Image: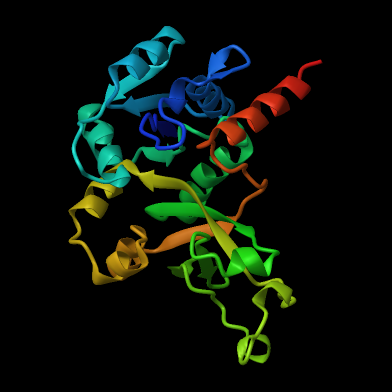
Length: 255
């Protein structure tokens, strides 16, 4: 079995209070909660520092853990939940974002099973990158693993470098990419006890440069397993446009 923790994500610049945005009669956060239940999770916790969100979540039967209103990171907020609920060290925890109402339950279960299968302290997923435009986008995190799926490195820089095609490239948007690129997806599985260790490790020059918190784990020599996601998850909702899109999709799926 495993536990899912869903960060509410109330704070948003272009879509403030999005966790409570209505999507076909239910707040977006409730959709994520229901997808979590459909993944086979034995426990689903909504974590938030917002009283209004907590009240709404409890109203649809969700266990809620209030997180402190500090500066600390997301991983830092996951640790606080583990500590406050006294979650045993070996419990498998899957972190899913509160603004992904269309997250495929199958991939939530996938990362959880992978954590147990390979017995690592941290597991994640990736999806193929097909466009050069996305490949060179620093916002798309590229990842590479060894033959067993154990991560070599994560980076905003393009890896692997294609010698023959990248040498004196003049138009990246027109380069034909090989089938070797992977975009890391921000869905994780951890052993509850490891999160505590993760946050205890000192900040690294590496993570500060790439602005990738997960590099702290690689820097400290901890094995991470990454596998191709069984299904490509939709981008999280953060704009009114994205919200309209999800509403249209859920509207189409019921008639």
